């Protein structure tokens, strides 16, 4: 069994550049920046599929 | 005349004070017993009690 | 199709014990199937009916 990727998901090649240190609510969280939207996501929760 | 109402068998001054006490007992600041909780799975960035 | 009579082998059962506040971390998460469960006392169906 290989789970299919669900219809809404977006392909993203891993690259060191996608992850960074950043301030977020008095913490230096490992922010991830989505390559399409450009949006930064300090929490692992709430990230785009 | 004393017999017409027992006045709860309390002294006059006790009733007079009792009114003030009732004003204390219903003050919002005292009312720190809370009812109900919302269970929800959420990150606690920037907590506030409120 | 038939019901198993012998004791079946089961996935390991980690009891998550969620509280009002906690620090979630997923370093050394198991990759194999695992039964996360929240409460410690789940042997609740005690009263056998003959």
Image (cartoon, coloured by chain):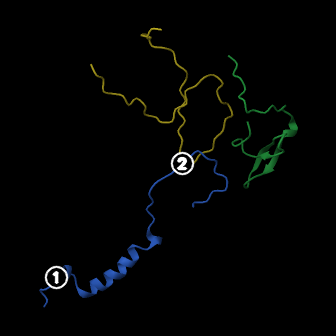
Chain colours: A green, B blue, C yellow
Residue B44, given in percent of the width and then of the height, sits at 63, 51
Compared with B3, A20 (above or below) is above
Residue C26 location (% of width, % of height)? 67, 35
Q: Chain of mark 2?
A: C
- In the displayed structure, B39 sits above or below B3; it is above
Q: Quadrant of the N terminus of chain A?
A: top right
Judge by depth and name the residue closer to the eye, B6 or B13: B6
| Disc 1 crowd, CA 10 A, few/some/many (<14, 14-19, 20+) | few
In-front residue for pair A17/A33: A33
Write down the quadrant of residue C36 in the picture.
top right
Disc 1 sits on a residue from what chain? Answer: B
Identity of the residue drawn at 44% across and 57% down: B35
Q: Secondary structure at mark 1?
A: loop
Residue bearing mark 2: C20
In this view, the residue farthest toward the front is A7
> What is the quadrant of the C terminus of chain A in the image?
top right
Q: Is residue A31 above or below residue B13?
A: above
- Residue at the image position 28 percent from the left and 87 percent from the top: B13
**Left or right: B49, with A18 as reference point:** left
Residue A46 lies in what quarter of the image? top right
Q: CA distance from mark 2 to mark 1?
A: 52 Å
Image check: A12 left or right of C17?
Answer: right
The residue identified by callout 1 is B6
Horizontally, residue B16 falls left or right of residue A31, namely left
Up the image or down, B4 lies above or below B43; here it is: below
Name the foreground residue: A47 vs A8: A8
Q: Residues within 10 Å of mark 2 (few under 14, many from 20)?
A: few
């Amino acid at each position: 069994f290989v789970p299919d990727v669900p219809e809404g998901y977006v392909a993203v090649q891993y690259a060191h550049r996608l992850f960074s240190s950043s301030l977020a609510n008095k913490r230096n969280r490992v922010t991830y920046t989505h390559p399409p939207t450009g949006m930064a996501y300090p929490s692992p929760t709430g990230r785009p599929h | 005349e004393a017999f017409r109402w027992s006045r709860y068998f309390l002294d006059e001054l006790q009733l007079r004070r009792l009114s003030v006490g009732l004003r204390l007992i219903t003050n919002p600041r005292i009312a720190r017993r809370f009812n109900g909780v919302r269970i929800m799975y959420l990150t606690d960035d920037d907590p506030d009690p409120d | 199709d038939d019901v198993g009579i012998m004791q079946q082998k089961k996935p390991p059962t980690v009891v998550q014990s969620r509280t009002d506040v906690f620090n979630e971390q997923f370093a050394n998460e198991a990759l194999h199937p695992t039964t996360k469960v929240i409460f410690n006392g789940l042997d609740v169906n005690t009263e056998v009916q003959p």
